[PDB]
Amino acid sequence: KAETSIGVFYVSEYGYSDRLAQAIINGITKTGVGVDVVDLGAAVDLQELRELVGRCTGLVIGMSPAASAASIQGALSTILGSVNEKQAVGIFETGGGDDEPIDPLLSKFRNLGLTTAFPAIRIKQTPTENTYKLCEEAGTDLGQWVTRDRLEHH
Image (cartoon, rainbow, N blue to C red; front, top):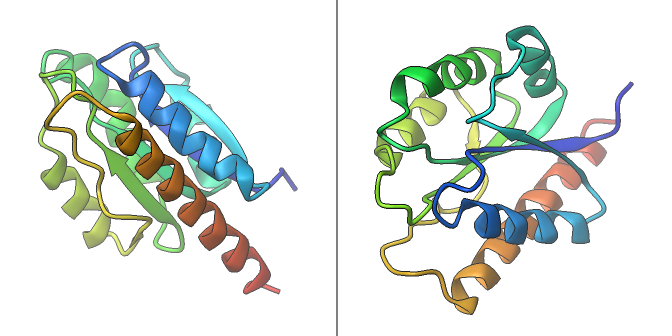
């Protein structure tokens, strides 16, 4: 009975995550689809985190630092076990220099049945406006997919 939303999970202030996620969110917003932002760096209630993922039709994940593995894996593992095959998920690199391998995570979601929301956004160089314009379009794509999924539901 909660508003149709897409969950955006990433570590705030890590690399260009803040701006990369914001661009994607702006693209989502255009479609009128809601969004819930969760900071992977800040401690979260595992049970409410499962509930949030549970009510999200779409998902967006930002890579975490390979330096905060121990502390971050708790939330990450929870998301992997709280997700369902009926949703779509997109993943972006941060350009922070300590990103965890994106591919391994991409494959974990695909193995679970989820659909890839958009081509995993990779950052090898400092983000440009063409970079953020790409995130914006990926955000829109997912937002449109979510809309079509809801309408294709009933």
